[PDB]
Amino acid sequence: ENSEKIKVNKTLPYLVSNVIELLDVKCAVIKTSTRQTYFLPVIGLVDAEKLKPGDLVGVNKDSYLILETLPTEYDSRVKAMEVDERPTEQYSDIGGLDKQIQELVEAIVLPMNHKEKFENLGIQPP
Amino acid sequence: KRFDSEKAGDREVQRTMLELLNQLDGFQPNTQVKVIAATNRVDILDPALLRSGRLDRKIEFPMPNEEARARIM
Amino acid sequence: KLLEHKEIDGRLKELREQLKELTKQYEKSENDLKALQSVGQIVGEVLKQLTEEKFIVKATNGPRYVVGCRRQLDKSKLKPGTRVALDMTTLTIMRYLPREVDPLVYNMSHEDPGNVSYSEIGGLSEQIRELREVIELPLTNPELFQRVGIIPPKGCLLYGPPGTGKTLLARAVASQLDCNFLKVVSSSIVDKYIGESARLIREMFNYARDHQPCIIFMDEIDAIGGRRFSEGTSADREIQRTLMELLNQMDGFDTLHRVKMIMATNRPDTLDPALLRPGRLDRKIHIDLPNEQARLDILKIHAGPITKHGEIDYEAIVKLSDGFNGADLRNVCTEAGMFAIRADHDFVVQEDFMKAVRKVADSKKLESKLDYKPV
Ligand SMILES: Nc1ncnc2c1ncn2[C@@H]1O[C@H](COP(=O)(O)OP(=O)(O)OP(=O)(O)O)[C@@H](O)[C@H]1O
Ligand SMILES: [Mg+2]
Ligand SMILES: [Mg+2]
């Protein structure tokens, strides 16, 4: 069977579609990325509970059928705003702003490393 | 700042702010994403964006007085 | 003999058990192979019944087709508008389907994990009683209002200064009550497509109409609301249409029964003078900045769960906090801990609470204290 099972997946090109309604009359209704809706009677090679309405799922190009659950997608613009090369500017580089640098490190950095402290006093971090 | 008017206006940008407002603190108590904002004109900001639930610790950054200019150099 | 293979039987049993489990997975795999031969089906809605074996169906992607019907499928539930799945090669109805629920609408309902109680929204006591008079009372004892002869109000607008209790109050009813409660950002329902923005509102009420006792809490409404510019912009007449759809499904040719709406806004003046008309948003609650009595009530709730020590005086904070809407009062509590956390104190005192009351008041002068009431 595995040889035949891979044969359908061996057609690597999938058609990304978003699950619209996981009807239980354990079926699924999908909306391929071509503005076409469908009523896959059998979910396919994926669990009937791992699929929640709105998830991204790949579909066989010719016989539409769910084969995998792709990871959630984010706009290309939003991914380019995550810094990977950390800037090199120590706190000693900033001058004069001593009463303000501390006030920030204790509201955006400290509450991120000493969660045991706020929960001990029961104050939601700012 | 939001702006009431007839005969044309600008609400396309206002929706983005309105989505920022609710995402920061609305119908969901997200407590792991910390928001830092930078601005050099606070008079123009919408009063809704300067609440306590939204950006909370409003720091004032003043010009160097007479010693910050020594360390700054 | 006396022993025989009784002792040797242990090895055989262990080997068989391990191999037996392997064959179990083979049955599971066969199930998947039985699903690779099932193809999808185009989805469209029936328009008319030309004859017994001929139907007019429009696939919800493209053109209109005249297609047949499967013999077994009954030909009495295929009324106009019924969603029907069609075969891929020879278009023929093979199943009648329930009305679809847009995934956005599904995400618009199963939302709230907060579970906020009525005991947390202090200060607003009369407001809650007024709001519960148009959400709970008409949906539990309808026979009362059939006595007098009035029809219970449909809408509700919760306006006020930016920081009083509006969303907190709305979430309160969201955690309470036993009726469907749609929560919408009021700005996540607009997309760039030509008609998708309007369609999300037709489904929102269609789902509400299908599921009775439902409350549609549209959040900040200055986004999809507006004043209907004359001489607007290209991508601003479109948002206008969406308002004209949310507007017409409130009070139009088909009165909406047993679906109440709650709307909130921090600037109830930019709203079109059609959304504010009585009949659509009948009652207009005016959640305001807490008064002297309320202000004290606010502090206890958020200052309660604090590792305090000493005669923490809540009377002192209230007099010095005028205009503290609803969060800097909670900011006062949280900021106070910040002063306490400095000095390495698991120890909150009254002075820290006072030391945070001014630090919040100082950071409030840069706001623009404007009333901005509806008209
Ligand atoms: N009566 C009250 N009791 C407790 N907390 C309150 C009260 N009034 C206001 N708050 C505080 O207000 C905060 C935010 O309230 P909420 O977001 O509902 O107000 P809002 O800014 O008017 O809302 P929105 O901008 O979403 O229309 C909450 O975290 C809560 O602590
Ligand atoms: Mg608000
Ligand atoms: Mg209308």
Image (cartoon, coloured by chain):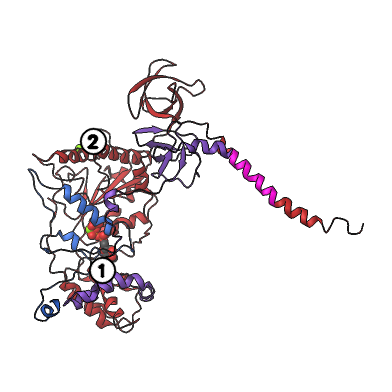
Chain colours: A purple, B blue, C red
Between circles 2 and 1, the one closer to the viewer is 1
Label 2: element kind: loop
Q: How many marks?
A: 2
In magenta segment, residue C364: no
The disc numbered 1 marks a residue on which chain? A
Disc 1: which residue: A88
Quadrant holding the C terminus of chain B: bottom left
- The three-letter amino acid code for the residue at tag 1 is Thr
Residue C180 appears anywhere in the view: no
Q: Is residue C27 magenta?
A: yes
Q: Position of residue B29 (x, y in %)?
A: 33, 61
Image position of A46 with respect to B62: above or below: above
Residue, x 30% and y 55% (percent of image)?
A: C170
Residue C175, percent from left and from top: 37, 56
Q: Quadrant of the N terminus of chain B?
A: bottom left
Q: Nearer the viewer, residue C231 or C285?
A: C231
Above or below for B64 versus C140: below
State left or right for residue C249 relative to residue C100. left
Q: Are marks 2 and 1 on the same chain?
A: no
Q: Most prominent secondary structure in the magenta stretch?
A: helix
Please give left or right for residue C196 compared with residue C175 in the image: left
Residues at marks 2 and 1 touching, judged by CB atoms closer than 8 Å: no
Q: Secondary structure at mark 1?
A: loop
Q: Residue type at mark 2?
A: Ile
Magenta range: C18-30
Residue C87, position in %: x, y? 45, 25
Looking at this view, is C247 or A60 the one in front? A60
Q: Which residue is labeled 2 in the image?
A: C194
Mark 2 and mark 1: Cα distance apart in space:
47 Å
